[PDB]
Length: 574
Ligand code: VO4
Image (cartoon, rainbow, N blue to C red; front, side, top):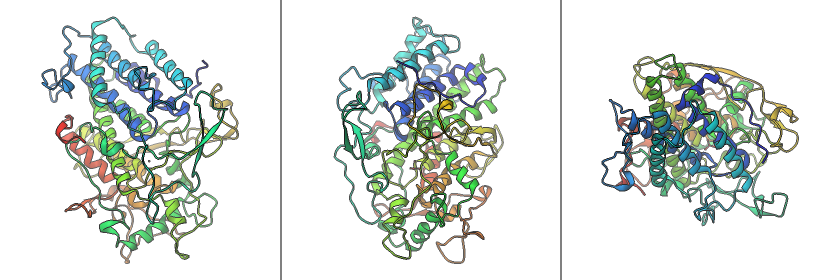
């Protein structure tokens, strides 16, 4: 088959001389390729799960052969429970080959054709071409691997055994099933997107030019409540969103949120849009909304973490440094596991409340002096395509981006504290990064004038090129914040989906009503002054709970870290 020409990644090629980074890279490539061809593990929660599984297998394969001192492996060889029993090296001492076997085995199990019956129902929607393209990626990776891959070595075989264990234990085949789910219309209730109420999908994925059929997607409605958690030691909950349950009386907050939604996230040319050009840039920068050649948010978070890892490595040699190898293997396991669990809990809460998106909220408001029946958002960018595709929708509260970001960046902060600088674990850090480029704004990717052509490189396809923006960030606290508010700029999330409005916005004399500038744009607090302290109530439980995705993510990362990356006790699994 013709290999899809993938655009160049903005990153020092030296990074991939390190075999831990190389395998992470392979995972990211499969991430973007599967979203281009419509293969398995698409969507934010499951794409995160794939990376978590990959790095867990790598972590244990490496630390089995090169034992750590301040922590231990995720699974152990002495576990009585066969499902959690880690294989023993038994002579194998080649860490490079162990990692290769674990990574290759895991990625292959994840992305290859489900010959073992699983093709029915679960995989019955992916074309043969999708699988073929994914295979190409896997095949050339073997050839590009630093130091090569010796599939016959005992160490390689050991890595494979490790992968088998993790795959059998954590794989969730029916994770994205929506069978049986249907929206329950009403105020504050999630339903089909007014701009994309239905999709025409081919009856046969192998014949895309053939007959289509109407389809209504709902992204992983049962995943969060039924899936196996990775390293969390408890269930996490958020306060009821403004307008629902115990907080149904928070009308001032809700009304002002509608107001901020229109002004900050509307389409570019609307007279009601007050968002600045720079804010529009911040919105698109963090998107990665499953587009062609781009993938999902977990991919971007890993791209950023790769830069942090190299920027703050202990030793200069990326190729032959066990200090670096152990550092990266540990960091990525921590980060990708936190990201996986963040996906689980954000999805659990999303479908629990089933809160509607701003587009529907503003349009269906019903009050002549509050709503706008014809409003349009800036929206999730449909990069490298010529239209606005129907992307499987899901509820608004809390923001997936916000939760992912909170988890990933708080994990990075906990890991580097005392090493890059010193700070209170709940206060701004100093982990700065430079020359960070998002593929949404890289001067290469674009909004096509005609349908995407997978046999030609993106540069030879007509369209409006996305401006190349090179960013610098002063801290992981800033990254966390901007990643969260970017969704407000796109108009896909309410302010409270990110965090409590009180913690991120500038207050006025009027309660629940926040400050706007001379031209009506919403004013945010300075990043250095932001503290996620405001909590709220839940109708079904006593106590105070976090509001929005960022606080939820921070909470998940702290828990995992404090427990040193230990499996969720099987007793508390769904
Ligand atoms: O991925 V949101 O849940 O931030 O659209």
